[PDB]
Length: 212
Length: 215
Figure 1 (cartoon, rainbow over the protein chains, first blue to last red):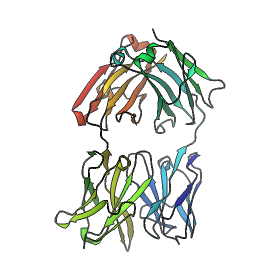
Figure 2: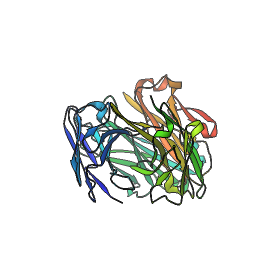
Figure 3: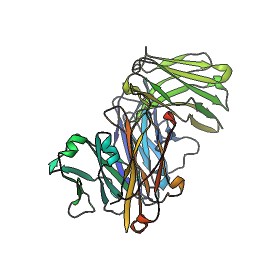
Figure 4: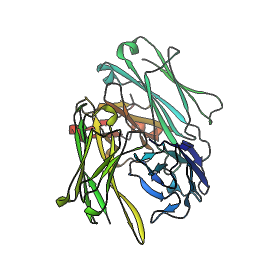
C-alpha cells in the first residue's frame, strides 16, 4: 500500500495568514491526489482532485499542486471557518490511502489557564472509587503540563486528560485531568495536589486539598 | 441536492458482524459508485471499498477482503456494507460517499456517518457526581461509567450556556466511558442561585438532573 506522509501534523496560524501543507507519497502517484477538509463531528469535504483542480464551490484561496511523489496544499487568506483538519489521499492505485492529517488551529495571544481542583464526592466514595479532577480553563496555546501529587508522590498511569476543541469565540482551550484511585488508596493519603505549567505562567501554579 | 442517509448507531460484541445502510436520493442511483470510509475515534480516514449499484460489482481494501461484503438494493436506492468478525479496532464512524462529475460541476456527497462500537461492554447509565465549587468560581458534574456513547449534558435545563465546557468522553480501561462538564459562574451567586446539570443517556433511557451545591 502506497503510504502518504503529511507534514506537519499540527499547525498554528493567524486569520489572514497563508499556510502550506505537504504530503509525500511512498511511490509515484502521478497527479492522482485528492485533498479533503474535515471539521469535528462532520463528514469530510472534498477540495482538490487531480492534485490541482478544485471541486465545485471550493474558493480560490485553496490551491493544490505537485506531481509524482511531492504534493502541497496552500491555503492563503485564512478565514476562521478554514481552521480544521486536512487530509491528502492518493487514488493512483488500490487500496486508496490517506495521509495522517494536519490540524490547523488559530493563533492568538498567550493566555494562562485558571486552575481548579475538585475532591471526590462522598456519593462517589460510597461506590468504592475516588476520582480527583483538575481543571485548566480558557488557556492558549494548547500545550499544558499537569502533575498529580498525592502525599508528594508523582502519579503515573492512573490519570487521563481530555481537552476541548478550540473555542469559537475566544480561541482558548480547556483541559481536564482526572485521577482515579481506589477508595482504600484514597483513604491512605492526605494531600492531593495538581501542578500546572504553561507558557502563560512564569512559575508553576499549584492547587491542592487535604482529604477532610 | 444529492443526499445520503445512513442507518443508526450500532453496538456489537467482538466476533459479531454489523450491516450499515446508505440510502441515496437525488440522482441516478445506478450510475455512480458508493465508497465507504471509516474513522476511528481520534484517528485518520481509512478506505474500505466501493460498490457500483448498477451491476453489483465491488472492490475492497485488501486489509478487509474476506471480511467485508458490500450489497445494494436498487429498488430502494440503498447500498449496504457488512463487516464481519468484528474486533475492538473496528470501532469507528462509517461514511458512505459518492461523486458526481458533470460538464459544469464536480461535487462529492457524504452520508451523516454511522457509529459502530465493538465492545464486550453492556449498556449502563452514567453515575453523575457533583464537582462542588471551592469572583469567578468553577463547578461541574462528573459523568462516569456509561456505555455506549453518547451522553448529552446541559445546565439549568438549557438556560446556563455561557462559560460551559463539556469535555469529550474518554474510554476507561473498564470498557466504560467517562466525561466531565464544567461551568464558571460568579463567585457571589454560589449561595443564592441554584445550578443543575442535566445528563441524558438515550441508550439506557437515563435522565439525571444533579444539583451541584457548595459542600
